Length: 40
Length: 49
Image 1 (cartoon, rainbow over the protein chains, first blue to last red):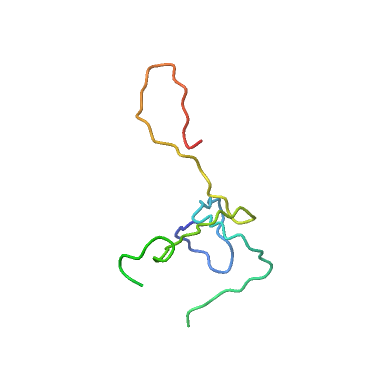
Image 2 (tube, helix red, strand yellow; image 1 turned 60 degrees about the horizontal axis):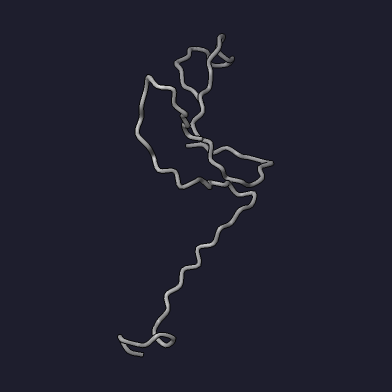
């Protein structure tokens, strides 16, 4: 993951930005599908 | 029973800690006792393995 202030909204910002490791949990189970969660 | 029960009849507390080695992560390491640090000498070093 990474964080940075931006100004673009509808398109990706122009440039490069590395993502540093944050978690490497050895969960040890299969993953095939996923879903997101939102705050309303 | 009695607080001073003899062997064989007194309560026997057992723990059966079981070593499992499978697809699960293997956080198995050695009995490494951390040593001090030296410098400016030819030395056989070992850091985190």
